[PDB]
Length: 96
Image 1 (tube, one colour):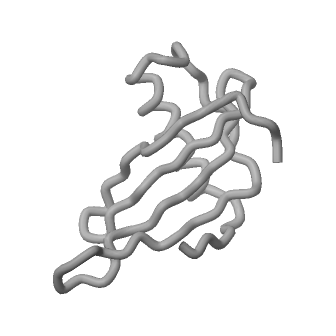
Image 2 (cartoon, rainbow, N blue to C red; image 1 turned 90 degrees about the horizontal axis):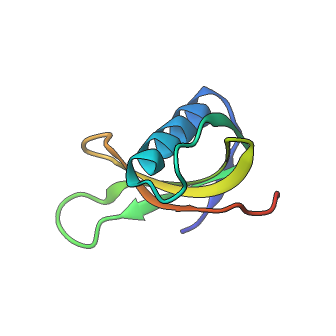
Protein backbone atom coordinates (compact mmCIF):
# COMPACT_ATOMS: atom_id res chain seq x y z
CA UNK A 1 0.00 0.00 0.00
CA UNK A 2 1.51 0.63 2.26
CA UNK A 3 -0.90 0.62 5.20
CA UNK A 4 -0.30 2.89 8.06
CA UNK A 5 -2.38 3.45 11.11
CA UNK A 6 -4.26 6.52 12.07
CA UNK A 7 -5.60 6.98 15.47
CA UNK A 8 -9.35 7.34 16.06
CA UNK A 9 -11.30 10.54 16.49
CA UNK A 10 -13.95 12.51 14.65
CA UNK A 11 -12.53 11.56 11.29
CA UNK A 12 -12.91 7.79 12.04
CA UNK A 13 -16.26 8.14 13.66
CA UNK A 14 -17.48 10.00 10.47
CA UNK A 15 -16.16 7.09 8.32
CA UNK A 16 -17.88 4.54 10.50
CA UNK A 17 -21.24 6.31 10.29
CA UNK A 18 -20.80 6.44 6.52
CA UNK A 19 -20.07 2.73 6.38
CA UNK A 20 -23.15 1.84 8.46
CA UNK A 21 -25.42 4.07 6.42
CA UNK A 22 -24.15 2.61 3.21
CA UNK A 23 -24.45 -1.07 4.44
CA UNK A 24 -27.94 -0.38 5.71
CA UNK A 25 -28.99 0.64 2.20
CA UNK A 26 -27.63 -2.76 0.80
CA UNK A 27 -29.75 -4.69 3.32
CA UNK A 28 -27.73 -7.89 3.81
CA UNK A 29 -27.14 -7.25 7.61
CA UNK A 30 -30.53 -5.72 8.21
CA UNK A 31 -30.74 -2.26 9.81
CA UNK A 32 -27.66 -1.58 11.88
CA UNK A 33 -27.19 1.19 14.49
CA UNK A 34 -23.76 2.83 14.58
CA UNK A 35 -21.97 2.56 17.92
CA UNK A 36 -18.22 3.27 17.64
CA UNK A 37 -15.08 2.91 15.53
CA UNK A 38 -12.20 1.37 17.53
CA UNK A 39 -8.49 1.07 17.02
CA UNK A 40 -6.81 -0.03 14.86
CA UNK A 41 -7.79 2.15 11.94
CA UNK A 42 -5.36 2.22 9.07
CA UNK A 43 -5.03 4.09 5.81
CA UNK A 44 -3.26 3.57 2.50
CA UNK A 45 -2.74 5.59 -0.62
CA UNK A 46 -4.56 4.61 -3.82
CA UNK A 47 -2.42 5.59 -6.81
CA UNK A 48 -3.74 6.35 -10.23
CA UNK A 49 -2.99 3.81 -12.94
CA UNK A 50 -2.39 6.43 -15.66
CA UNK A 51 -2.73 10.06 -16.49
CA UNK A 52 -1.42 13.30 -15.01
CA UNK A 53 -2.47 12.83 -11.42
CA UNK A 54 -0.40 10.77 -9.08
CA UNK A 55 -2.87 9.97 -6.31
CA UNK A 56 -6.41 8.68 -6.87
CA UNK A 57 -7.34 8.78 -3.22
CA UNK A 58 -7.07 6.85 0.02
CA UNK A 59 -8.44 3.62 1.40
CA UNK A 60 -9.39 3.20 5.05
CA UNK A 61 -9.97 -0.02 6.83
CA UNK A 62 -12.12 0.32 9.99
CA UNK A 63 -13.35 -1.85 12.87
CA UNK A 64 -16.86 -0.56 13.54
CA UNK A 65 -19.37 -1.62 16.15
CA UNK A 66 -22.94 -1.41 14.93
CA UNK A 67 -25.89 -2.94 16.79
CA UNK A 68 -23.33 -4.07 19.35
CA UNK A 69 -21.55 -6.33 16.84
CA UNK A 70 -18.05 -5.73 15.37
CA UNK A 71 -17.60 -5.38 11.62
CA UNK A 72 -14.69 -4.61 9.32
CA UNK A 73 -15.21 -2.05 6.60
CA UNK A 74 -13.10 -0.76 3.69
CA UNK A 75 -13.85 2.71 2.37
CA UNK A 76 -12.22 4.63 -0.41
CA UNK A 77 -12.10 8.36 -0.70
CA UNK A 78 -11.40 10.15 -3.97
CA UNK A 79 -8.59 12.73 -3.98
CA UNK A 80 -10.34 14.99 -6.60
CA UNK A 81 -13.97 14.74 -5.28
CA UNK A 82 -13.49 13.93 -1.68
CA UNK A 83 -16.27 11.38 -2.46
CA UNK A 84 -16.49 8.10 -0.46
CA UNK A 85 -17.31 4.54 -1.45
CA UNK A 86 -17.98 1.56 0.78
CA UNK A 87 -15.84 -1.12 -0.83
CA UNK A 88 -16.36 -3.82 1.68
CA UNK A 89 -18.25 -4.64 4.82
CA UNK A 90 -17.94 -7.97 6.70
CA UNK A 91 -18.64 -9.47 10.02
CA UNK A 92 -18.93 -10.11 12.84
CA UNK A 93 -15.16 -10.27 13.16
CA UNK A 94 -13.09 -10.77 16.07
CA UNK A 95 -11.78 -8.03 17.83
CA UNK A 96 -8.37 -6.77 17.29
